[PDB]
Amino acid sequence: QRLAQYGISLAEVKSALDASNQEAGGSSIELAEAEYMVRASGYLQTLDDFN
Amino acid sequence: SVLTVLWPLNKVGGEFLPQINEGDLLYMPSTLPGISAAEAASMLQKTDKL
Image (cartoon, rainbow over all chains, first blue to last red; front, top):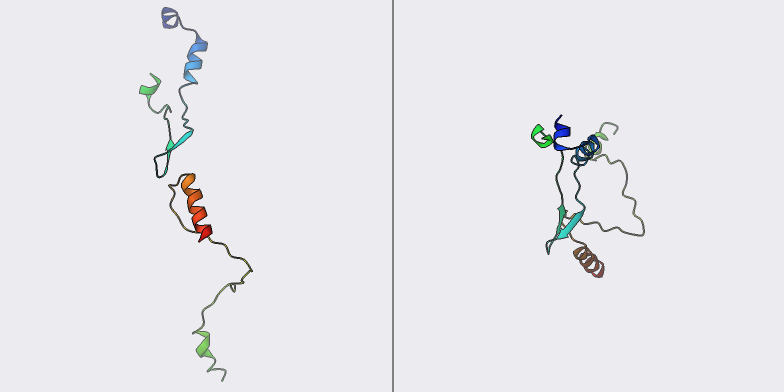
């Protein structure tokens, strides 16, 4: 009923679910003396994140 | 004499290998993690020239 109310399909739900449980950072910048690795969060940890 | 021979036995340590030398050497310094890519080349050139 709530899927029809807001007008959303199951494919969209699956795509948004499988695209929010990752963690990837692929850079490294030099602060004039040493390297600094760039990391980005995104994992699903608690129920507040699923919601 | 067989008894007197007990003096050096306890005065000599036990070692697994001798150090066998080769005609070459390998220099390896203990360092720290943080390092860039240009400073590494600079340090390498300095150590080689020294």
